[PDB]
Image (spheres, coloured by chain):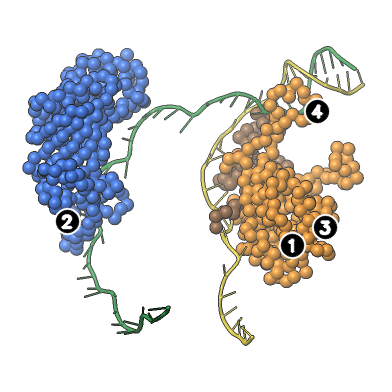
Chain colours: A orange, B blue, C brown, D green, E yellow
Amino acid sequence: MRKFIIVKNVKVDGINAKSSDITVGMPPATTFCGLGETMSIKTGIVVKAVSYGSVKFEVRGSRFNTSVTKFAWQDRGNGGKANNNSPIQPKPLADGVFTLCFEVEWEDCAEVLVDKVTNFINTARIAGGTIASFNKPFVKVAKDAEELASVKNAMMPCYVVVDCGVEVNIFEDAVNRKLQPMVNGYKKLEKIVDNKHMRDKFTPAYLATPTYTMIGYKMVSNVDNFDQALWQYGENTKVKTIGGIYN
Amino acid sequence: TKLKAPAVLAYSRKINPTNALMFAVNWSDRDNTTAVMVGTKTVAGTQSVRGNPNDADKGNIQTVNFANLPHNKNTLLVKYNVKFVGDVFKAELGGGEYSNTLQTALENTDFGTLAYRYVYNIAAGRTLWRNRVGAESIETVITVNDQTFTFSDLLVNEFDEDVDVAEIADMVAGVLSGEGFVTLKVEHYMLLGEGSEVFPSQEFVENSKLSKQLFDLNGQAAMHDQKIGNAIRTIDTWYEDATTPIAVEPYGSVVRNGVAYRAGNKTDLFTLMDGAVNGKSLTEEDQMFVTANLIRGGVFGG
Amino acid sequence: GNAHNLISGTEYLWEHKYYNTFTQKLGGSNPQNCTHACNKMRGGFKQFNCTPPQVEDNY
DNA sequence: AGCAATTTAAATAGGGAAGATAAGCAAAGGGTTGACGAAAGCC
DNA sequence: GGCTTTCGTCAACCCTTTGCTTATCTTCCCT
C-alpha cells in the first residue's frame, strides 16, 4: 500500500546543468534522490523513491555550446587581479519546469503533509537552481496497481526517466541504440584522509567518479509500470528504479 | 592600367511604371470606368504535343484564367504611371570612382531621342503587348504635370517625328539629364470591339491547377510593371544588323527568340562600359545604349 | 571526472558522427595550465547534450 | 394559439499539354574570461 | 618564517548545425 505526494509544474531556473564531466543537461536521478533525502532530513518525512519528469527544460546556450557563467572574484588573495575578468570554470546553467512525485509514508492528515512539502520546496533548490514557482502539491495513494497508474497519470504532462541499462559502455550504445546517458550513482576511488576542508568532519568521505546508466525519456502515461520511473537509493552507492530496466 | 569594374557595381531602375490596371470603357464615355475582372474558365480540347502522336486524340482539359471586355463596352482602358527618375549615373550600389568615370565618359549622350523613344513607346502603345493586335484605333492620353497629350495613330516599329512626343520627351530628357523626376499618367483606349478579349500579364505559378493564371489586382485584370517597363525600354535599334527595336538588355538578349543580339559581337554593355572607362571614345548610339542600360538598371560586376 | 570518458568520448563521438552533444574547452583561454589533454585537444571536449524532450504547451 | 406528412432516387466517361529559364557580386571582426612558478618586499 | 603581491612561464584545434518523445476518453446494468 503506497502513498505519494506530487508537486506539479516546478519551474526552476539556474539549474546546474553540469550533471558530470561528460553529461550536461537534465539533472540525473542522483540529484532528485538527494532532494528526496534532503526532505527526509529537514521535514522528517522519510522518502523511499522519487519519480521526476521534465515538463520543460532548456540548457542555456546554443545547440552545440552552453552559455558559460560570468564568474565573480570570490577567492581570497587574488586582489589586484579583481579588476580584470574572473576566469571561467565550466558550469553550464539551465532552466527547467519539472513534475516531482515522492513516495512517502505518512500517518497524519494530507494537509500537514502538503504544508510540510510546501515548506521544504519553498526552501529547496532543484539541482542548484532556485525554484521559481510550483503548484500546490497534492497527495494521491496507490492502493492497487490501477491506483498506482492513477498516481502515474496525475503527473501529466511530464517526461519521466526510465532506466534502460548498460550493454557495453556509454558512448557505444548512445550512438547505436540512441538512448540518453545520466548519472545513476558514483564509484568510490579512494578514502579521503583530510576532513578539515569538508562539510562534516565525522561523515566519511570518498573521492568518486560518476557511474552512468543509459536512460530513455517516455511520457508518464506511456510508461506501463510506474515502478520503472520511481528512482531510489540502491545499495551499491548508486540509484536505481523500483521496476528495474525498462523493456 | 585597365580600370576594372567593381563587383558591387549596380544601377537602379530609373523608369518605374506602376501595375497597368485594365478597365473597360466605351469609345464615347471614357469616364464610365468599369474594371475588367479576371475570370477562370476550364476548356476542353486536344493535346497536340510535338512528340506525342498517341495522346493526340485522348483529350485535354485546361483551366485558364481569361479576361474579356464586357459585351456593353468596346474599349479597353489601361491605366498606369510611368515615373522617370533622374540622377541616372549615381550607382546606388556601385563604387564612387568607376561610376564617376562612367558618368564623365557619358555626359554627351543624346538624351533627347532616348527620351523620345521612351515616350514614343508609351504613346504608340507598346505597353499594350497583345492588347493592340486587332484595334480600330489606339488613343493614348498622357498627363505630364498638368499637361494632357493625345495620341491617335503612331506606328510602333519606327520612331516618327511629331511635336507631342518631343514635347513630353523635353522634360523627360531634362529629368534624365539631371536631377528630379517626372510622372507620366498614361491612359490607353483601344477600340477592341464589343465583348473582345483582352490580354493581361500572366503570372508564373509552378504547382498550380491553372494552366494560365493572369495577374489580378483585387480581381481586376492588370499588367505587370516589368512588362510595361520592358515595353518602355524596347528602343534598341543600334545592335548588329538591327531590323526591329529590341529591349535594352546588358547582352541585348531576348528570351522568346532564343538569341542575344549583342553577345559575341563585342557590342554588349560590359565591353562598352570597360571601353568608356578606359578611354575608348564611344559612338552616339553606343553611348545611348549604355545609358539606356544605366537607367534600366542592373548589377554589372564580377 | 573520468579522463578516459572525456578523451575517448570526444574521439569516438567525433568518429561515430554523434552530434547530440555539447563542446567545451576546459582550461579557458590557454588550457595548458589545466591538463595535457586540454593543452592538446584545444577544440574542446565532447559531452552529452542531456536535454530531455519538451512538452508542447498547445495541445 | 399550435398545427406544415410520408418513400424514391440524385449519371455513367474522356481528358487534365509540354518547352524555356531559376544571376552574378561582397561582406560574415575581435575585445575579457591563467594557474602554477618564481623573484621579492613585508609583517 | 611564512606571506602576500606582481611578474615571468608555457602553450597551440579537425570539425557537427535537430530530434530525444510525441498527453491521462464507455461496454453491461438497474435504479
Give neighbour class at mark 4: few <14, some 14-19, many 20+ (Cα, 10 Å): few
Which residue sits at x=73%, y=64%?
Answer: A140
Instruction: Check disc 3 and report the residue beneath it.
Output: A45
Amino acid type, mark 3: Ile
Instruction: Check disc 2 and report the residue beneath it.
Output: B48
Q: Earlier in the sequence, mark 1 or mark 4?
A: 4
Q: How far apart are marks 3 and 1 (CA)?
A: 13 Å
| Residue A189 found in image quarter | top right
Instruction: Check disc 1 and report the residue beneath it.
Output: A139
Instruction: Check disc 4 and report the residue beneath it.
Output: A76
Relative side of A26 to B241, left or right: right
Residue A168 spot, x, y in % from top left: 67, 54
**Residue A8: mark:** none
| Residue B273 found in image quarter | top left
User: Closer to the camera, A194 or E20?
Assistant: E20
Q: How far apart are marks 4 and 2 (CA)?
A: 91 Å
Dot 2: chain letter:
B
With respect to residue A145, does A138 lie above or below? above
User: Closer to the camera, C35 or B74?
Assistant: B74
User: Closer to the camera, A204 or A68?
Assistant: A68
Which residue sits at x=72%, y=53%?
Answer: A29
Residue A202 spot, x, y in % from top left: 91, 45
